[PDB]
Structure formats: C-alpha cells, structure tokens
Amino acid sequence: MNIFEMLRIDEGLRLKIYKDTEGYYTIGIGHLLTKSPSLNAAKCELDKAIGRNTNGVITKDEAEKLFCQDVDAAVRGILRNAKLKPVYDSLDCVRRAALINMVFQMGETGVAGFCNSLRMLQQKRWDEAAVNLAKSRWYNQTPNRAKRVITTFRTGTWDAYKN
Ligand SMILES: [Cl-]
Ligand SMILES: [Cl-]
Ligand code: NA
Ligand code: NA
Ligand code: NA
Ligand code: NA
C-alpha cells in the first residue's frame, strides 16, 4: 500500500464527468473540475486540464496523469502551509499519507484550520487525535473514508485498506 493505492481506493476511477460526494463535477480519480453548477464550465476545465477536446470523456492514462499531478499538488500545498508542514514533517511515512489524503479531499485551508487535531497529531497522541478528528463535518459526511484515514493516523498501519 502507498498514497496512490490508498487514494485510488477512496476516490475510485471514472472516465466520464461525474458528481463527487458534494455534488461537484469531477473526473478520473477524484479530480475536481469546478464547483460551478454549469456542466459547460466543467467541460472547459476538463479540456484545459487534458489539452484536447475531450467531450467529457478521458482515458485511464489521462486519469492517472491528473492523479499524479493532484497528489503532488496536495504534498506541495502541505509543504507551503505554516500549519500543516510541521505536522507533516513530524509524521512517519504511513501517517503522512493519511494527511495527504485529507488535503486531497478537503483542501489545504480546511485541514490547516483543525488546530486541536493537528496539535494532537504532532504530539503523537494517536488515540486522542483519532477521537478529535471524528468531531468533524468530514467524518459525518464521509464516515467510511474518514474511519479508514483515522485508523491510519491511529495505528500508523495500512490495516484499514486491507481487503
Ligand atoms: Cl477554463
Ligand atoms: Cl464514506
Ligand atoms: Na453525487
Ligand atoms: Na486525480
Ligand atoms: Na491531548
Ligand atoms: Na493517545
């Protein structure tokens, strides 16, 4: 298991424009296109992202290319953020993937505001952090995914992504 396999489990793979769990136009492995309600706006974003006239459909290779970029962008967003970088730097490789997963799903700004959960993670108070992370809109709206990510923070293992 690694961050790519983990996000592929959590995000799935779809080759045509779909709506994510928040109702927003998306494609591939959780590549958010736009928050605009306009499908035409989403199609412009898609053609721009892929570099061709896609008609709302992409290939697996194209989806994986966007995914490469999006994982990289989540990591760069962590490293540039004054609240997230110290936490990321304090974590082991497996728990770093859990933090990347959160940022991929919710964005840097949202995660960076969880000052209590972040402190508990940096303090390595894993069970406390896990309880605190569940007191979130994130956990309530996507509980199965959040449980997997939280178990990853709690244990430092990939156990929640087996089977
Ligand atoms: Cl555009
Ligand atoms: Cl879920
Ligand atoms: Na939906
Ligand atoms: Na992606
Ligand atoms: Na505490
Ligand atoms: Na603890």
Image (spheres, grey):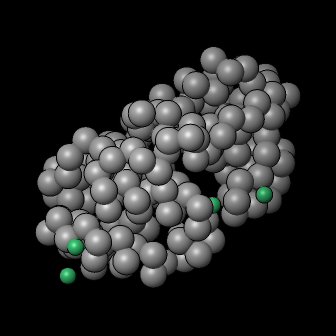
- Pick the residue in front: 62 or 53: 62
Expressed as whole percent of the image width and height from the top left, the position of residue 138 reads 53, 70
- Pick the residue in front: 126 or 76: 126
Looking at the image, residue 123 sits to the left or right of residue 41; the answer is left
Expressed as whole percent of the image width and height from the top left, the position of residue 94 reads 30, 44
At 29% from the left edge and 72% from the top edge, which residue is drawn? Answer: 127
Determine which quarter of the picture holds residue 71.
top left
Rendered position, 155 above or below 1: below
Looking at the image, residue 7 sits to the left or right of residue 18; the answer is left
Expressed as whole percent of the image width and height from the top left, the position of residue 80 reads 26, 50
Expressed as whole percent of the image width and height from the top left, the position of residue 21 reads 70, 59
Question: Which quadrant of the render holds ligand 5?
Answer: bottom left
Determine which quarter of the picture holds residue 76.
top left
Rendered position, 138 above or below 98: below
At 26% from the left edge and 59% from the top edge, which residue is drawn? Answer: 84
Number of marks in the rendered image: 0
At 29% from the left edge and 51% from the top edge, which residue is drawn? Answer: 156
Looking at the image, residue 95 sits to the left or right of residue 36; the answer is left
- Pick the residue in front: 18 or 120: 120
